[PDB]
Length: 301
Length: 296
Ligand SMILES: C[C@]1(O)CCN(c2nc(N3C[C@H](O)[C@@H](O)C3)cc(C(F)(F)F)c2C#N)C1
Ligand SMILES: C[C@]1(O)CCN(c2nc(N3C[C@H](O)[C@@H](O)C3)cc(C(F)(F)F)c2C#N)C1
Image 1 (spheres, each protein chain N blue to C red):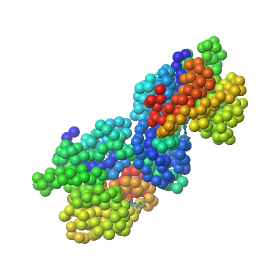
Image 2: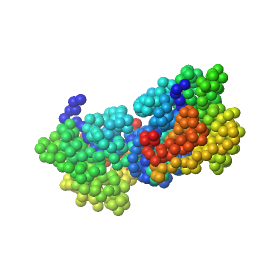
Image 3: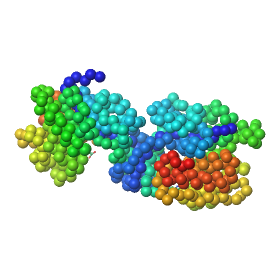
Protein backbone atom coordinates (compact mmCIF):
# COMPACT_ATOMS: atom_id res chain seq x y z
CA UNK A 1 0.00 0.00 0.00
CA UNK A 2 0.72 3.77 -0.06
CA UNK A 3 3.29 4.82 2.60
CA UNK A 4 3.32 8.61 3.19
CA UNK A 5 6.65 10.39 2.46
CA UNK A 6 9.01 10.66 5.50
CA UNK A 7 6.77 8.64 7.84
CA UNK A 8 8.70 5.41 8.61
CA UNK A 9 11.64 4.27 10.79
CA UNK A 10 13.67 1.58 8.98
CA UNK A 11 15.71 -1.03 10.86
CA UNK A 12 18.33 -2.95 8.85
CA UNK A 13 19.73 -6.14 10.33
CA UNK A 14 19.16 -9.75 11.42
CA UNK A 15 15.93 -11.77 11.81
CA UNK A 16 16.32 -15.30 13.28
CA UNK A 17 13.86 -18.01 14.48
CA UNK A 18 14.86 -18.92 18.03
CA UNK A 19 13.62 -22.30 19.29
CA UNK A 20 13.81 -22.16 23.11
CA UNK A 21 13.55 -25.41 25.11
CA UNK A 22 13.39 -25.55 28.90
CA UNK A 23 14.93 -28.81 30.24
CA UNK A 24 15.14 -30.51 33.73
CA UNK A 25 18.86 -31.22 33.11
CA UNK A 26 21.26 -30.66 30.15
CA UNK A 27 20.91 -33.56 27.64
CA UNK A 28 23.79 -36.04 27.34
CA UNK A 29 24.99 -36.70 23.78
CA UNK A 30 22.98 -39.47 22.00
CA UNK A 31 19.94 -39.19 24.29
CA UNK A 32 16.22 -38.63 23.53
CA UNK A 33 14.69 -36.31 26.15
CA UNK A 34 11.45 -34.40 26.79
CA UNK A 35 11.57 -30.65 27.45
CA UNK A 36 9.36 -29.02 30.12
CA UNK A 37 8.39 -26.31 27.55
CA UNK A 38 9.32 -25.12 24.05
CA UNK A 39 8.81 -21.68 22.42
CA UNK A 40 9.39 -20.50 18.83
CA UNK A 41 10.27 -16.82 18.85
CA UNK A 42 11.26 -14.20 16.30
CA UNK A 43 14.69 -12.81 17.33
CA UNK A 44 17.46 -10.55 16.01
CA UNK A 45 18.49 -6.98 17.03
CA UNK A 46 16.88 -4.98 14.18
CA UNK A 47 13.88 -7.35 14.32
CA UNK A 48 13.41 -6.80 18.13
CA UNK A 49 13.71 -2.98 17.70
CA UNK A 50 11.01 -3.14 15.00
CA UNK A 51 8.56 -4.77 17.45
CA UNK A 52 9.35 -2.09 20.09
CA UNK A 53 8.83 0.81 17.55
CA UNK A 54 5.42 -0.66 16.55
CA UNK A 55 4.34 -0.89 20.20
CA UNK A 56 5.63 2.69 20.74
CA UNK A 57 3.23 3.91 17.95
CA UNK A 58 5.73 4.38 15.08
CA UNK A 59 5.16 3.20 11.43
CA UNK A 60 8.16 0.96 11.04
CA UNK A 61 9.80 -1.24 8.50
CA UNK A 62 12.33 -4.08 8.60
CA UNK A 63 15.11 -4.69 6.07
CA UNK A 64 16.89 -7.99 6.28
CA UNK A 65 17.60 -11.25 4.49
CA UNK A 66 15.17 -14.14 4.24
CA UNK A 67 14.95 -17.26 2.01
CA UNK A 68 11.46 -18.50 0.97
CA UNK A 69 10.18 -21.39 3.08
CA UNK A 70 8.38 -22.35 6.29
CA UNK A 71 10.82 -20.53 8.70
CA UNK A 72 10.46 -17.18 6.76
CA UNK A 73 6.62 -17.66 6.83
CA UNK A 74 6.63 -18.02 10.65
CA UNK A 75 8.91 -14.91 10.93
CA UNK A 76 6.72 -12.82 8.51
CA UNK A 77 3.47 -13.75 10.29
CA UNK A 78 5.18 -12.82 13.62
CA UNK A 79 6.43 -9.45 12.13
CA UNK A 80 2.86 -8.81 10.84
CA UNK A 81 1.43 -9.86 14.25
CA UNK A 82 3.61 -6.95 15.60
CA UNK A 83 2.49 -4.42 12.90
CA UNK A 84 5.91 -4.46 11.13
CA UNK A 85 6.08 -3.56 7.35
CA UNK A 86 7.98 -6.46 5.61
CA UNK A 87 8.03 -5.00 1.95
CA UNK A 88 11.85 -4.27 2.09
CA UNK A 89 12.90 -7.85 2.93
CA UNK A 90 15.81 -8.90 0.66
CA UNK A 91 14.55 -12.32 -0.45
CA UNK A 92 17.35 -14.79 -1.34
CA UNK A 93 17.48 -17.66 -3.86
CA UNK A 94 20.42 -19.32 -1.97
CA UNK A 95 20.86 -20.16 1.76
CA UNK A 96 18.79 -20.99 4.92
CA UNK A 97 16.64 -18.40 6.86
CA UNK A 98 18.49 -18.09 10.24
CA UNK A 99 17.30 -20.44 12.98
CA UNK A 100 18.82 -21.02 16.48
CA UNK A 101 18.40 -23.72 19.09
CA UNK A 102 18.52 -22.55 22.74
CA UNK A 103 18.57 -25.01 25.62
CA UNK A 104 17.79 -23.57 29.05
CA UNK A 105 18.55 -25.69 32.13
CA UNK A 106 15.69 -25.28 34.67
CA UNK A 107 18.02 -26.30 37.58
CA UNK A 108 21.09 -23.94 37.20
CA UNK A 109 19.52 -21.46 34.70
CA UNK A 110 22.36 -21.83 32.11
CA UNK A 111 21.73 -21.18 28.40
CA UNK A 112 23.34 -23.41 25.72
CA UNK A 113 23.07 -21.97 22.21
CA UNK A 114 23.46 -23.63 18.78
CA UNK A 115 23.68 -20.52 16.54
CA UNK A 116 22.26 -20.23 13.01
CA UNK A 117 24.44 -21.25 10.07
CA UNK A 118 26.41 -18.75 7.84
CA UNK A 119 24.63 -19.82 4.54
CA UNK A 120 22.27 -16.83 3.96
CA UNK A 121 23.83 -13.71 2.33
CA UNK A 122 23.48 -10.40 4.27
CA UNK A 123 21.75 -7.30 2.78
CA UNK A 124 24.11 -5.77 0.17
CA UNK A 125 24.84 -2.22 -0.96
CA UNK A 126 23.27 -3.15 -4.37
CA UNK A 127 20.10 -4.46 -2.62
CA UNK A 128 20.00 -1.11 -0.68
CA UNK A 129 20.45 0.95 -3.96
CA UNK A 130 17.11 -0.40 -5.28
CA UNK A 131 15.27 1.11 -2.21
CA UNK A 132 13.32 4.36 -2.59
CA UNK A 133 14.31 6.17 0.64
CA UNK A 134 11.65 8.95 0.59
CA UNK A 135 9.14 7.05 2.81
CA UNK A 136 11.75 6.98 5.66
CA UNK A 137 12.32 9.71 8.28
CA UNK A 138 14.98 7.60 10.14
CA UNK A 139 17.23 4.66 9.16
CA UNK A 140 18.74 2.45 11.89
CA UNK A 141 21.53 0.01 10.89
CA UNK A 142 22.57 -3.00 13.04
CA UNK A 143 26.31 -3.44 12.35
CA UNK A 144 27.02 -6.79 10.58
CA UNK A 145 28.69 -6.74 7.05
CA UNK A 146 30.40 -3.32 7.64
CA UNK A 147 32.15 -2.76 4.23
CA UNK A 148 28.69 -3.10 2.50
CA UNK A 149 26.79 -1.10 5.21
CA UNK A 150 29.38 1.76 4.87
CA UNK A 151 28.20 2.18 1.22
CA UNK A 152 24.47 2.18 2.31
CA UNK A 153 25.39 4.92 4.83
CA UNK A 154 27.21 6.89 2.01
CA UNK A 155 24.02 6.54 -0.12
CA UNK A 156 21.95 8.15 2.73
CA UNK A 157 24.52 11.02 2.97
CA UNK A 158 24.13 11.63 -0.82
CA UNK A 159 20.29 11.58 -0.49
CA UNK A 160 20.50 14.09 2.41
CA UNK A 161 22.91 16.53 0.62
CA UNK A 162 20.05 17.17 -1.90
CA UNK A 163 17.26 17.68 0.71
CA UNK A 164 16.08 20.70 2.72
CA UNK A 165 16.83 20.09 6.50
CA UNK A 166 13.13 19.18 7.20
CA UNK A 167 13.31 16.28 4.62
CA UNK A 168 16.67 14.91 5.77
CA UNK A 169 16.71 11.25 6.93
CA UNK A 170 18.26 10.85 10.45
CA UNK A 171 20.63 7.89 10.85
CA UNK A 172 21.63 5.55 13.72
CA UNK A 173 24.19 2.75 13.88
CA UNK A 174 24.61 -0.07 16.45
CA UNK A 175 28.01 -1.71 17.17
CA UNK A 176 27.02 -4.58 19.43
CA UNK A 177 29.49 -7.38 18.51
CA UNK A 178 33.18 -7.07 19.53
CA UNK A 179 34.42 -7.51 15.87
CA UNK A 180 37.18 -5.17 14.49
CA UNK A 181 35.42 -4.85 11.08
CA UNK A 182 32.43 -3.16 12.84
CA UNK A 183 34.53 -0.39 14.48
CA UNK A 184 34.62 1.61 11.17
CA UNK A 185 30.84 2.19 11.58
CA UNK A 186 31.46 4.61 14.53
CA UNK A 187 32.30 7.22 11.85
CA UNK A 188 28.75 7.10 10.39
CA UNK A 189 25.33 8.12 11.66
CA UNK A 190 23.89 10.98 13.76
CA UNK A 191 23.47 8.43 16.62
CA UNK A 192 25.93 5.63 17.41
CA UNK A 193 24.99 2.97 19.98
CA UNK A 194 27.94 0.99 21.41
CA UNK A 195 27.22 -2.06 23.62
CA UNK A 196 28.62 -2.62 27.18
CA UNK A 197 30.12 -5.93 25.81
CA UNK A 198 32.02 -4.04 23.01
CA UNK A 199 33.17 -1.34 25.51
CA UNK A 200 34.44 -4.03 27.99
CA UNK A 201 36.24 -5.82 25.09
CA UNK A 202 37.92 -2.49 24.17
CA UNK A 203 39.14 -2.27 27.82
CA UNK A 204 36.66 0.29 29.21
CA UNK A 205 35.29 -0.35 32.68
CA UNK A 206 32.30 2.10 32.66
CA UNK A 207 29.95 3.94 30.26
CA UNK A 208 31.82 7.22 31.10
CA UNK A 209 35.22 5.64 30.14
CA UNK A 210 33.72 4.10 26.93
CA UNK A 211 32.10 7.38 25.80
CA UNK A 212 35.23 9.52 26.56
CA UNK A 213 37.60 6.94 25.01
CA UNK A 214 35.50 6.42 21.80
CA UNK A 215 34.00 9.88 21.02
CA UNK A 216 36.99 10.68 18.76
CA UNK A 217 35.87 7.80 16.45
CA UNK A 218 32.52 9.49 15.51
CA UNK A 219 31.65 12.10 12.82
CA UNK A 220 31.29 15.84 13.72
CA UNK A 221 28.00 16.49 15.54
CA UNK A 222 27.23 12.78 16.28
CA UNK A 223 25.86 11.52 19.64
CA UNK A 224 27.56 8.38 21.09
CA UNK A 225 25.29 6.25 23.40
CA UNK A 226 26.25 3.49 25.90
CA UNK A 227 23.77 1.49 28.09
CA UNK A 228 25.45 -0.26 31.09
CA UNK A 229 22.64 -2.64 32.37
CA UNK A 230 21.69 -1.69 36.03
CA UNK A 231 24.08 1.33 35.91
CA UNK A 232 21.69 2.98 33.38
CA UNK A 233 22.88 4.78 30.29
CA UNK A 234 25.08 7.66 29.13
CA UNK A 235 25.18 9.82 25.98
CA UNK A 236 27.88 12.22 24.72
CA UNK A 237 27.38 14.89 22.06
CA UNK A 238 29.53 17.55 20.29
CA UNK A 239 29.21 19.94 23.31
CA UNK A 240 31.40 17.57 25.45
CA UNK A 241 28.77 17.20 28.21
CA UNK A 242 28.44 13.61 29.46
CA UNK A 243 24.68 12.97 29.90
CA UNK A 244 23.40 10.23 32.16
CA UNK A 245 20.18 8.43 33.24
CA UNK A 246 19.93 5.88 36.07
CA UNK A 247 18.26 2.56 35.20
CA UNK A 248 14.57 2.02 36.11
CA UNK A 249 14.81 -1.63 37.35
CA UNK A 250 11.60 -3.69 37.66
CA UNK A 251 10.43 -5.00 41.16
CA UNK A 252 11.66 -8.46 40.02
CA UNK A 253 13.77 -9.18 36.90
CA UNK A 254 11.96 -11.70 34.61
CA UNK A 255 13.47 -11.37 31.08
CA UNK A 256 16.39 -9.17 29.96
CA UNK A 257 16.61 -10.66 26.46
CA UNK A 258 16.05 -7.86 23.97
CA UNK A 259 16.19 -5.12 26.67
CA UNK A 260 19.18 -3.62 24.77
CA UNK A 261 17.04 -3.50 21.60
CA UNK A 262 14.19 -1.94 23.61
CA UNK A 263 16.61 0.78 24.81
CA UNK A 264 17.83 1.44 21.22
CA UNK A 265 14.29 1.64 19.68
CA UNK A 266 13.01 3.87 22.55
CA UNK A 267 15.99 6.26 22.21
CA UNK A 268 15.47 6.38 18.37
CA UNK A 269 11.68 6.86 18.81
CA UNK A 270 12.08 9.72 21.37
CA UNK A 271 14.75 11.49 19.20
CA UNK A 272 12.56 11.07 16.04
CA UNK A 273 9.73 12.79 18.03
CA UNK A 274 11.88 15.96 18.52
CA UNK A 275 12.80 15.19 22.16
CA UNK A 276 16.26 16.09 23.53
CA UNK A 277 19.16 13.64 24.06
CA UNK A 278 18.63 13.77 27.91
CA UNK A 279 14.85 13.10 27.43
CA UNK A 280 15.62 10.22 24.92
CA UNK A 281 18.18 8.65 27.36
CA UNK A 282 15.61 8.78 30.22
CA UNK A 283 12.71 7.37 28.12
CA UNK A 284 14.99 4.57 26.76
CA UNK A 285 15.94 3.59 30.34
CA UNK A 286 12.28 3.64 31.47
CA UNK A 287 11.05 1.42 28.56
CA UNK A 288 14.03 -1.04 28.77
CA UNK A 289 13.50 -1.22 32.58
CA UNK A 290 9.80 -2.06 32.26
CA UNK A 291 10.75 -4.76 29.64
CA UNK A 292 13.13 -6.56 32.08
CA UNK A 293 10.23 -7.40 34.44
CA UNK A 294 8.06 -8.76 31.59
CA UNK A 295 8.31 -11.93 29.52
CA UNK A 296 8.64 -10.83 25.87
CA UNK A 297 7.41 -7.46 24.58
CA UNK A 298 3.72 -7.44 25.71
CA UNK A 299 2.92 -4.50 27.99
CA UNK A 300 6.24 -2.59 27.60
CA UNK A 301 4.13 0.59 26.84
CA UNK B 1 -3.52 -57.16 1.75
CA UNK B 2 -1.09 -55.07 -0.36
CA UNK B 3 -0.13 -52.20 2.07
CA UNK B 4 1.99 -51.99 5.26
CA UNK B 5 0.48 -49.73 7.94
CA UNK B 6 2.64 -47.93 10.55
CA UNK B 7 0.80 -46.74 13.66
CA UNK B 8 2.78 -44.18 15.71
CA UNK B 9 4.04 -40.56 15.86
CA UNK B 10 4.77 -37.92 13.26
CA UNK B 11 6.96 -35.09 14.75
CA UNK B 12 8.67 -32.13 13.06
CA UNK B 13 12.45 -32.61 13.47
CA UNK B 14 14.18 -29.22 13.52
CA UNK B 15 17.76 -30.29 12.81
CA UNK B 16 21.11 -28.55 13.47
CA UNK B 17 24.23 -30.26 12.15
CA UNK B 18 27.28 -29.51 14.36
CA UNK B 19 30.98 -30.48 14.07
CA UNK B 20 31.12 -31.12 17.87
CA UNK B 21 28.53 -31.66 20.64
CA UNK B 22 28.11 -28.32 22.53
CA UNK B 23 29.46 -28.18 26.10
CA UNK B 24 26.82 -26.89 28.61
CA UNK B 25 26.62 -23.04 28.90
CA UNK B 26 28.56 -22.70 25.55
CA UNK B 27 27.75 -21.01 22.22
CA UNK B 28 28.59 -22.84 18.92
CA UNK B 29 27.53 -22.08 15.30
CA UNK B 30 26.00 -24.99 13.35
CA UNK B 31 27.31 -26.19 9.95
CA UNK B 32 23.79 -26.47 8.40
CA UNK B 33 20.10 -26.58 9.41
CA UNK B 34 17.10 -28.51 7.94
CA UNK B 35 13.55 -29.55 8.75
CA UNK B 36 12.71 -33.20 8.53
CA UNK B 37 9.50 -35.18 8.98
CA UNK B 38 10.22 -37.42 12.00
CA UNK B 39 8.43 -39.71 14.43
CA UNK B 40 9.43 -43.41 14.51
CA UNK B 41 6.41 -44.83 12.62
CA UNK B 42 6.62 -41.86 10.24
CA UNK B 43 10.37 -42.50 9.50
CA UNK B 44 9.61 -46.25 8.91
CA UNK B 45 7.01 -45.17 6.22
CA UNK B 46 9.70 -43.05 4.46
CA UNK B 47 11.99 -46.11 4.36
CA UNK B 48 9.13 -48.51 3.26
CA UNK B 49 8.23 -46.09 0.43
CA UNK B 50 11.91 -45.82 -0.72
CA UNK B 51 12.05 -49.69 -0.65
CA UNK B 52 9.10 -49.68 -3.08
CA UNK B 53 6.49 -50.91 -0.56
CA UNK B 54 3.03 -49.19 -0.67
CA UNK B 55 2.46 -48.13 2.94
CA UNK B 56 0.18 -46.04 5.08
CA UNK B 57 0.67 -43.98 8.20
CA UNK B 58 -1.79 -43.69 11.08
CA UNK B 59 -1.19 -41.13 13.82
CA UNK B 60 -2.53 -37.95 15.42
CA UNK B 61 -2.06 -34.60 13.63
CA UNK B 62 -3.33 -31.07 14.48
CA UNK B 63 -4.20 -28.75 11.55
CA UNK B 64 -1.73 -25.91 10.99
CA UNK B 65 1.29 -24.78 8.89
CA UNK B 66 3.55 -27.50 10.41
CA UNK B 67 1.05 -30.36 9.65
CA UNK B 68 0.89 -28.87 6.10
CA UNK B 69 4.72 -29.38 5.90
CA UNK B 70 4.40 -32.97 7.25
CA UNK B 71 1.47 -33.87 4.93
CA UNK B 72 3.26 -32.46 1.83
CA UNK B 73 6.35 -34.56 2.77
CA UNK B 74 4.24 -37.76 3.27
CA UNK B 75 2.62 -37.23 -0.18
CA UNK B 76 5.93 -36.47 -1.97
CA UNK B 77 6.98 -39.97 -0.67
CA UNK B 78 3.71 -41.69 -1.64
CA UNK B 79 2.67 -42.35 1.97
CA UNK B 80 -1.12 -42.81 2.32
CA UNK B 81 -2.37 -40.38 5.01
CA UNK B 82 -6.13 -41.27 4.70
CA UNK B 83 -5.92 -43.03 8.12
CA UNK B 84 -4.62 -39.92 10.02
CA UNK B 85 -6.51 -39.07 13.27
CA UNK B 86 -6.94 -35.23 12.81
CA UNK B 87 -7.39 -33.44 16.19
CA UNK B 88 -9.37 -30.26 17.07
CA UNK B 89 -7.27 -29.66 20.26
CA UNK B 90 -3.44 -29.67 20.67
CA UNK B 91 -0.35 -28.47 18.76
CA UNK B 92 1.81 -30.59 16.41
CA UNK B 93 4.87 -32.00 18.33
CA UNK B 94 8.33 -30.82 17.35
CA UNK B 95 11.85 -31.57 18.49
CA UNK B 96 15.25 -29.95 18.30
CA UNK B 97 17.76 -32.42 16.92
CA UNK B 98 21.48 -31.91 17.27
CA UNK B 99 23.43 -34.16 14.86
CA UNK B 100 27.16 -34.44 15.45
CA UNK B 101 28.77 -34.61 12.00
CA UNK B 102 32.00 -36.21 13.30
CA UNK B 103 30.35 -39.44 14.63
CA UNK B 104 26.63 -39.27 13.69
CA UNK B 105 25.42 -39.07 17.30
CA UNK B 106 21.96 -37.53 17.38
CA UNK B 107 20.50 -35.82 20.44
CA UNK B 108 16.72 -35.18 20.54
CA UNK B 109 14.92 -32.59 22.75
CA UNK B 110 11.26 -33.45 22.15
CA UNK B 111 8.31 -31.14 22.75
CA UNK B 112 5.29 -33.42 23.45
CA UNK B 113 2.18 -31.24 22.90
CA UNK B 114 -0.72 -32.98 24.80
CA UNK B 115 -2.04 -33.98 21.24
CA UNK B 116 -4.37 -36.92 22.10
CA UNK B 117 -3.03 -40.30 20.96
CA UNK B 118 -4.61 -42.67 18.37
CA UNK B 119 -7.27 -44.72 20.28
CA UNK B 120 -8.86 -48.21 19.90
CA UNK B 121 -11.97 -46.22 18.65
CA UNK B 122 -9.86 -44.50 15.92
CA UNK B 123 -8.42 -47.97 15.11
CA UNK B 124 -11.94 -49.58 15.00
CA UNK B 125 -12.76 -47.33 11.95
CA UNK B 126 -9.84 -48.78 9.89
CA UNK B 127 -10.56 -51.24 7.00
CA UNK B 128 -8.11 -54.05 7.90
CA UNK B 129 -8.50 -55.80 4.49
CA UNK B 130 -6.05 -53.41 2.63
CA UNK B 131 -3.14 -54.40 4.95
CA UNK B 132 -0.48 -57.15 4.42
CA UNK B 133 1.37 -56.03 7.63
CA UNK B 134 0.60 -53.68 10.57
CA UNK B 135 3.47 -52.12 12.63
CA UNK B 136 2.71 -50.50 15.98
CA UNK B 137 5.06 -48.00 17.64
CA UNK B 138 4.66 -48.51 21.44
CA UNK B 139 3.12 -45.30 22.92
CA UNK B 140 -0.36 -45.66 24.68
CA UNK B 141 0.09 -49.35 25.69
CA UNK B 142 -3.36 -50.19 27.31
CA UNK B 143 -5.13 -48.52 24.30
CA UNK B 144 -2.78 -50.25 21.76
CA UNK B 145 -3.26 -53.71 23.40
CA UNK B 146 -6.98 -53.27 22.40
CA UNK B 147 -5.90 -52.39 18.78
CA UNK B 148 -3.75 -55.60 18.80
CA UNK B 149 -6.64 -57.77 20.19
CA UNK B 150 -8.77 -56.46 17.24
CA UNK B 151 -6.18 -57.65 14.62
CA UNK B 152 -5.92 -61.07 16.39
CA UNK B 153 -9.77 -61.30 16.33
CA UNK B 154 -9.74 -60.48 12.54
CA UNK B 155 -6.99 -63.12 12.00
CA UNK B 156 -9.05 -65.98 13.61
CA UNK B 157 -11.84 -65.29 11.03
CA UNK B 158 -9.28 -65.54 8.10
CA UNK B 159 -7.47 -68.35 6.13
CA UNK B 160 -3.71 -68.70 7.04
CA UNK B 161 -2.78 -67.24 3.59
CA UNK B 162 -4.88 -64.07 4.24
CA UNK B 163 -3.53 -63.40 7.79
CA UNK B 164 -2.20 -59.92 8.73
CA UNK B 165 1.39 -59.99 10.04
CA UNK B 166 2.00 -57.81 13.11
CA UNK B 167 5.08 -56.01 14.45
CA UNK B 168 5.59 -54.11 17.70
CA UNK B 169 8.40 -51.64 18.68
CA UNK B 170 9.23 -51.24 22.43
CA UNK B 171 11.79 -48.37 22.13
CA UNK B 172 11.22 -46.33 25.34
CA UNK B 173 12.14 -47.93 28.74
CA UNK B 174 8.62 -47.34 30.17
CA UNK B 175 7.05 -50.29 32.19
CA UNK B 176 3.56 -49.49 30.69
CA UNK B 177 4.95 -50.64 27.25
CA UNK B 178 6.34 -54.03 28.44
CA UNK B 179 2.84 -55.57 28.08
CA UNK B 180 3.23 -55.18 24.26
CA UNK B 181 6.10 -57.83 24.30
CA UNK B 182 3.37 -59.61 24.49
CA UNK B 183 1.61 -59.24 21.13
CA UNK B 184 2.71 -59.52 17.50
CA UNK B 185 4.63 -61.93 15.26
CA UNK B 186 7.80 -59.71 15.41
CA UNK B 187 8.82 -57.71 18.52
CA UNK B 188 11.57 -55.07 18.26
CA UNK B 189 13.27 -54.28 21.57
CA UNK B 190 15.69 -51.33 21.72
CA UNK B 191 19.26 -51.40 23.09
CA UNK B 192 18.18 -48.60 25.57
CA UNK B 193 15.24 -50.78 26.82
CA UNK B 194 17.48 -53.92 27.02
CA UNK B 195 20.26 -51.99 28.91
CA UNK B 196 17.66 -50.45 31.35
CA UNK B 197 16.67 -54.08 32.18
CA UNK B 198 20.30 -55.04 33.04
CA UNK B 199 21.40 -56.64 29.72
CA UNK B 200 24.88 -55.97 28.28
CA UNK B 201 24.40 -57.50 24.77
CA UNK B 202 21.70 -58.29 22.18
CA UNK B 203 22.02 -62.08 22.77
CA UNK B 204 21.71 -61.65 26.61
CA UNK B 205 18.57 -59.47 26.09
CA UNK B 206 16.93 -61.94 23.66
CA UNK B 207 17.55 -64.99 25.94
CA UNK B 208 16.34 -62.94 28.95
CA UNK B 209 13.20 -61.44 27.31
CA UNK B 210 12.04 -64.33 25.04
CA UNK B 211 9.86 -65.62 27.94
CA UNK B 212 7.62 -62.50 27.50
CA UNK B 213 6.72 -63.00 23.78
CA UNK B 214 3.58 -64.61 22.24
CA UNK B 215 3.80 -68.28 21.05
CA UNK B 216 5.73 -68.43 17.74
CA UNK B 217 6.99 -64.79 17.76
CA UNK B 218 10.42 -63.47 16.68
CA UNK B 219 12.18 -61.15 19.17
CA UNK B 220 14.68 -58.74 17.43
CA UNK B 221 17.31 -56.51 19.15
CA UNK B 222 19.66 -54.15 17.21
CA UNK B 223 22.84 -53.03 19.06
CA UNK B 224 24.37 -50.13 17.04
CA UNK B 225 27.86 -51.11 15.65
CA UNK B 226 27.43 -54.64 17.15
CA UNK B 227 24.84 -55.34 14.41
CA UNK B 228 21.59 -57.05 15.36
CA UNK B 229 20.31 -60.39 16.75
CA UNK B 230 17.00 -62.28 16.47
CA UNK B 231 15.42 -65.23 18.41
CA UNK B 232 12.55 -67.44 17.30
CA UNK B 233 10.44 -70.39 18.50
CA UNK B 234 13.18 -72.91 17.44
CA UNK B 235 15.51 -71.48 20.14
CA UNK B 236 18.26 -70.66 17.58
CA UNK B 237 20.01 -67.34 18.04
CA UNK B 238 20.51 -65.47 14.78
CA UNK B 239 23.12 -62.72 14.33
CA UNK B 240 24.04 -60.11 11.69
CA UNK B 241 27.14 -57.94 11.64
CA UNK B 242 26.44 -54.23 11.10
CA UNK B 243 27.31 -52.57 7.75
CA UNK B 244 28.95 -49.31 9.09
CA UNK B 245 29.80 -46.62 6.52
CA UNK B 246 33.53 -45.56 6.56
CA UNK B 247 32.29 -42.09 7.80
CA UNK B 248 29.22 -42.26 10.19
CA UNK B 249 27.55 -38.76 9.75
CA UNK B 250 23.82 -39.14 10.84
CA UNK B 251 22.17 -41.87 12.97
CA UNK B 252 18.79 -40.02 13.26
CA UNK B 253 16.18 -42.54 12.17
CA UNK B 254 18.72 -45.45 11.82
CA UNK B 255 16.58 -47.53 14.25
CA UNK B 256 13.48 -46.74 12.14
CA UNK B 257 15.46 -47.62 8.95
CA UNK B 258 16.37 -51.01 10.49
CA UNK B 259 12.74 -51.80 11.69
CA UNK B 260 11.25 -50.90 8.30
CA UNK B 261 13.88 -52.92 6.33
CA UNK B 262 13.32 -56.04 8.57
CA UNK B 263 9.45 -55.62 8.10
CA UNK B 264 9.87 -55.21 4.31
CA UNK B 265 12.17 -58.25 4.02
CA UNK B 266 9.86 -60.54 6.10
CA UNK B 267 6.73 -59.21 4.22
CA UNK B 268 8.57 -60.29 0.98
CA UNK B 269 8.85 -63.88 2.32
CA UNK B 270 12.58 -63.83 3.16
CA UNK B 271 14.03 -65.74 6.14
CA UNK B 272 14.68 -64.08 9.57
CA UNK B 273 18.43 -64.42 8.88
CA UNK B 274 18.06 -62.58 5.55
CA UNK B 275 15.71 -59.88 7.01
CA UNK B 276 18.15 -59.18 9.92
CA UNK B 277 21.05 -58.79 7.45
CA UNK B 278 18.97 -56.52 5.13
CA UNK B 279 17.97 -54.36 8.13
CA UNK B 280 21.64 -53.91 9.11
CA UNK B 281 22.49 -53.19 5.46
CA UNK B 282 19.95 -50.41 4.91
CA UNK B 283 20.42 -48.94 8.45
CA UNK B 284 24.23 -48.79 7.87
CA UNK B 285 23.88 -47.19 4.43
CA UNK B 286 21.59 -44.53 6.11
CA UNK B 287 24.29 -43.70 8.80
CA UNK B 288 26.60 -42.49 6.01
CA UNK B 289 24.05 -40.01 4.64
CA UNK B 290 22.12 -36.94 5.88
CA UNK B 291 18.42 -37.94 5.93
CA UNK B 292 16.86 -40.81 3.97
CA UNK B 293 17.54 -40.08 0.28
CA UNK B 294 20.05 -42.39 -1.36
CA UNK B 295 19.58 -45.46 0.93
CA UNK B 296 18.46 -47.58 -2.15
C1 LIG C 1 19.60 -1.35 28.09
C2 LIG C 1 20.14 -2.40 29.05
O1 LIG C 1 21.43 -1.98 29.50
C3 LIG C 1 20.22 -3.79 28.41
C4 LIG C 1 20.28 -4.69 29.65
N1 LIG C 1 19.46 -3.99 30.64
C5 LIG C 1 19.40 -4.51 31.92
N2 LIG C 1 20.10 -5.63 32.13
C6 LIG C 1 20.08 -6.19 33.34
N3 LIG C 1 20.73 -7.40 33.46
C7 LIG C 1 20.74 -8.21 34.69
C8 LIG C 1 21.64 -9.39 34.40
O2 LIG C 1 22.96 -9.15 34.88
C9 LIG C 1 21.61 -9.50 32.84
O3 LIG C 1 20.49 -10.31 32.45
C10 LIG C 1 21.47 -8.06 32.37
C11 LIG C 1 19.38 -5.63 34.41
C12 LIG C 1 18.64 -4.46 34.18
C13 LIG C 1 17.83 -3.91 35.34
F1 LIG C 1 18.19 -4.41 36.53
F2 LIG C 1 17.95 -2.57 35.48
F3 LIG C 1 16.53 -4.15 35.20
C14 LIG C 1 18.59 -3.85 32.92
C15 LIG C 1 17.75 -2.71 32.71
N4 LIG C 1 17.06 -1.81 32.60
C16 LIG C 1 19.22 -2.60 30.24
C1 LIG D 1 19.52 -50.03 14.06
C2 LIG D 1 20.63 -49.31 14.81
O1 LIG D 1 21.08 -50.13 15.89
C3 LIG D 1 20.22 -47.94 15.32
C4 LIG D 1 21.55 -47.23 15.47
N1 LIG D 1 22.40 -47.82 14.44
C5 LIG D 1 23.73 -47.50 14.40
N2 LIG D 1 24.14 -46.70 15.39
C6 LIG D 1 25.39 -46.24 15.40
N3 LIG D 1 25.72 -45.43 16.44
C7 LIG D 1 24.70 -45.03 17.43
C8 LIG D 1 25.44 -44.00 18.27
O2 LIG D 1 25.32 -42.71 17.67
C9 LIG D 1 26.89 -44.51 18.21
O3 LIG D 1 26.99 -45.70 18.99
C10 LIG D 1 27.04 -44.85 16.73
C11 LIG D 1 26.32 -46.60 14.42
C12 LIG D 1 25.89 -47.46 13.41
C13 LIG D 1 26.92 -47.89 12.39
F1 LIG D 1 28.15 -47.53 12.71
F2 LIG D 1 26.97 -49.22 12.25
F3 LIG D 1 26.69 -47.35 11.17
C14 LIG D 1 24.57 -47.94 13.33
C15 LIG D 1 24.16 -48.73 12.20
N4 LIG D 1 23.80 -49.33 11.31
C16 LIG D 1 21.83 -49.06 13.91
